[PDB]
Image (cartoon, rainbow, N blue to C red; front, side, top):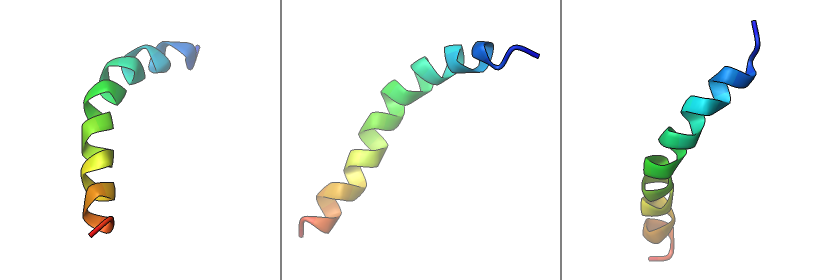
Length: 30
């Protein structure tokens, strides 16, 4: 199985996801 390989793809997806997760926080600040 080796679930460690899954993390490899999480490194690239988290980079772009970092902008989406913040977009919501900025809305709450209002």
